[PDB]
Amino acid sequence: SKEKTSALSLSNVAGVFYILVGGLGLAMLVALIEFCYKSRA
Amino acid sequence: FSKPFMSLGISIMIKKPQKSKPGVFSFLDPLAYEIWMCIVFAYIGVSV
Image 1 (cartoon, rainbow over the protein chains, first blue to last red):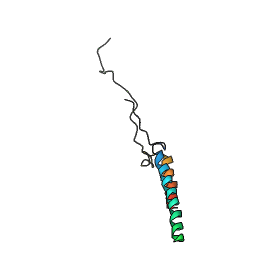
Image 2 (image 1 turned 90 degrees about the vertical axis):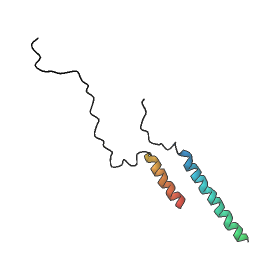
Image 3 (image 1 turned 135 degrees about the horizontal axis):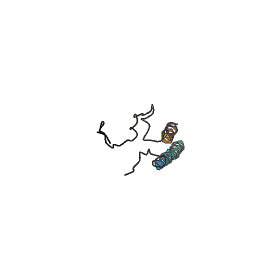
Image 4 (image 1 turned 120 degrees about the horizontal axis):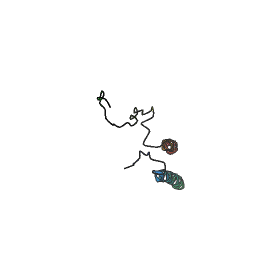
């Protein structure tokens, strides 16, 4: 019967920030390799 | 004993349920304050 009013901690949505930054560096990877190919062609 | 001059009974006393004080920052409650910062620092990060 003793249930609590608990806010979400950062651990609950923790991986969403991880796949945010992983999605950021992937776009950093693509923004490099799209300018390099047009500079070759 | 004499005649009953006052009628009474055993009842219950708890502390009164207090005034519902939300605070001036009650809408930020279901998410912890760490997450609201970690949104904003990541909000600037994605826009950068």
